[PDB]
Length: 259
Ligand SMILES: [Ca+2]
Ligand code: NA
Image (tube, rainbow, N blue to C red; front, top):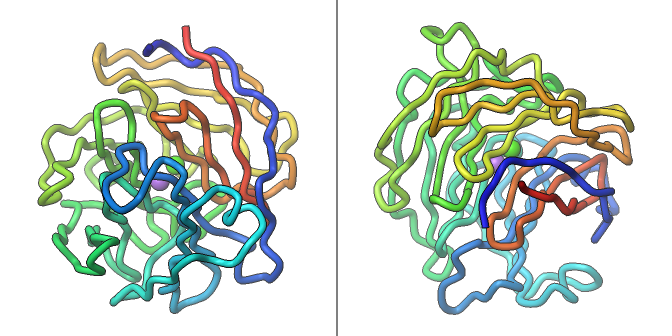
């Protein structure tokens, strides 16, 4: 079941974007799929530019890997950066030039909730180390939906909060001692936040852990390879128990092992 991260496998490339619009992006599957979607449904957002609204949806993995989308959704408001997730039928994304998270229900194309993440920096205040306006990073783990951010009161250290997926209320918050701008990205596995040291290196590491159950911080040295030298997005999927990442045009996955 659950445990501490102990190993990350080699990146596997599933699709490569063919234009610069996909240099950065987010791709994802739903770890709690709901009708009409399934555990194979995949979403892809190419996130370069200033008016990002198109969300590509694929019914089957084979379509994601080789074909055109099954459907394209046009979001009612432009999206910011690479932090979005899908969870239990909704895309959760940050509005451009805002600290607002939006719940967009995919089957009805309806905005169901919006919430300012209180005190969160946005638009280049507390990005990860590559920039990209990556101030606010949503995450799904075994327990549900979270948000990773920082605030002036936390002096740029990573803050994580559990979110109610229905109405986006913050349920509980934890403050780490990890400077968000000093790490390439982060993700949560089994209630532990992990960070990646570098977005360019073939020889990066998963370098810090913060366990929300115990409050304990640790250092780690688990190898992590950025095959294409520019990882813009690194998230965990708790149904597949894999990392999903976006690395310089390439949509990649990594296997992991937990103790
Ligand atoms: Ca992430
Ligand atoms: Na995310």
